[PDB]
Image 1 (tube, rainbow over the protein chains, first blue to last red):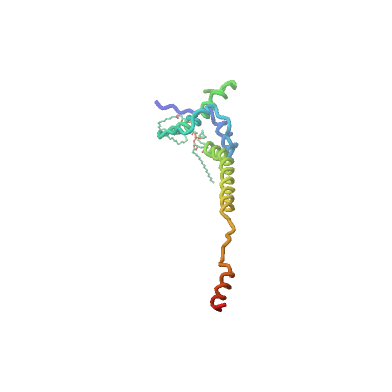
Image 2 (image 1 turned 30 degrees about the horizontal axis):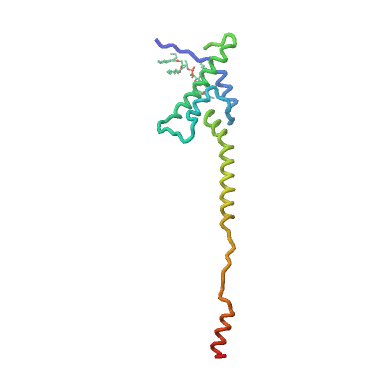
Length: 77
Length: 57
Ligand SMILES: CCCCCCCCCCCCCCCCCC(=O)OC[C@H](COP(=O)([O-])OCC(O)COP(=O)([O-])OC[C@@H](COC(=O)CCCCCCCCCCCCCCCCC)OC(=O)CCCCCCCCCCCCCCCCC)OC(=O)CCCCCCCCCCCCCCCCC
């Protein structure tokens, strides 16, 4: 069985393309703690502790495009 | 398309400020290394005195 369907973000994808063809600063992040792991200076980690930033940002964006807009009636998660 | 551009944009101001400060630091170091050199040369009075000794005066 193979089901062919589409996500409910097509309009949001269009808006993202329209509004983010040019650069813009980001200053408010839902989860800001992924960018500041160390609070005491002179402490450093040899492990790739900043690898999670990109996934965190993408997940926040995706889940926000879905959940927050789901309040609108008939919008589907 | 979205994330990396935004973070580069966020970076720009701090880097610009730090580079301006670095350039000012270079100029300050250039200025601080300038000193006027004063050289001392043999007083001609001794030369005149030696000339007198040659004159046998
Ligand atoms: C038998 C009947 C037919 C069906 C056959 C199927 C065969 C299946 C084989 C077996 C497969 C088994 C496994 C299946 C698993 C399915 C899982 C699934 O669906 O999960 C949901 C999940 C939902 O994903 P999503 O979140 O909705 O995002 C995916 C979207 O594509 C949007 O995501 P995105 O936006 O991130 O995507 C990137 C997007 C970036 O954005 C764009 O590029 C924008 C455009 C988006 C297009 C795609 C969206 C499609 C929207 C709906 C359809 C549009 C209208 C179609 C009209 C049809 C009319 C009949 O770029 C593209 O999409 C690149 C394509 C661009 C094409 C442009 C073509 C221009 C032509 C111009 C011609 C001009 C001619 C001029 C001549 C002049 C002469 C004078 O699906 C997927 O992840 C993809 C599943 C695909 C699996 C592979 C299937 C095999 C390939 C089949 C090809 C058939 C071609 C022939 C068809 C002929 C007509 C009938």
